[PDB]
Image (tube, rainbow, N blue to C red; front, side, top):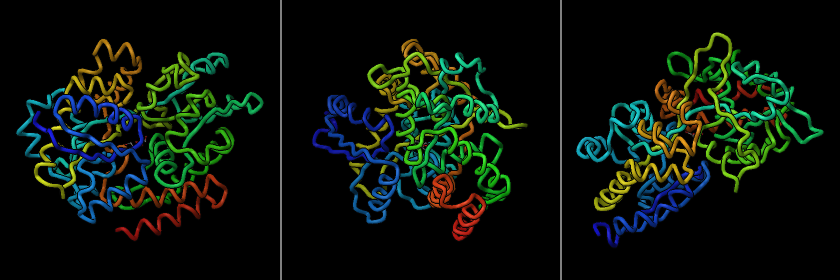
Length: 399
Ligand SMILES: OC[C@@H](O)[C@@H](O)[C@@H](O)CO
């Protein structure tokens, strides 16, 4: 087989695709003879360890799962192979027309160059407990104000029942969840010239309402949750509503992992007044480390093409990757039977906003700064105005 004797080392975010990539290693070795070693890490550790590998030119990782919001940093620093030529050369293998253009562009490209190739696309959705809403006589929320109101109505500590959950963990997790909320109210963290605007009066008001919501309606231990932690909370039955990525939805219908099978609805994220549908897109691309040997680059690209092929990518998603990205997947009889929320995913990608969160080179640093600020506010250590003022000062140093 062509890749006999080859080892590929892949650094992966600990989203559901980390375990699925680990599982698919066997089939990849059966198909190509290559040994795929997947190292799954949490978001911060992943970013730290792979950035150090790039900077040191040490060639420890051949393949890295690159977050959409890292695309500008990857392009500016040349961390990854520019895949533009190979995408064009091998397009017929990739069935590009069957990948939504917003996904190819936003998860793969920056400034017209492929720094990665999309392998896991996420739609921003509201997950809610159908049973709890029905019992309470409440309609499906469509406005962020409904979310606040319903979250309070559905909080009753006496039954260990919380109306709402979101991330509290310092850093990217807490930052991203506040950013999502702010986006749905038409807010931003950059001004119209792309410069930091973390502490605008709108954002201070937004964070003030968000803090009140978090303190009043989320499980008390939510101050420590990252994405996986709040997904687990929701699956366990603890919270009535959660704004999340579609990646979490396979888990809700898994009886081995879920106390809410049959109980969860998936809809578009609610919006503030005057705000049009936000169809937020996120996810991860697969990058090849620019430092590795030519034969390692060739093998890594062979792996990428294998993974995104219709056959394997369907298997990937039937195994729970929650990473749907192909038009063909949205009408596929098996995928639609297993995952009845794909109409919402498809509508999101058809209208997708691949700039739902910034992808500029400064963003990963902004994200960490904002994460410290929002966590200090949710923990009761700093007030919204002072915290965002401080964050703005630090963010401006990057420009
Ligand atoms: O599960 C968390 C998810 O991987 C992050 O929000 C990424 O930033 C999505 O692009």
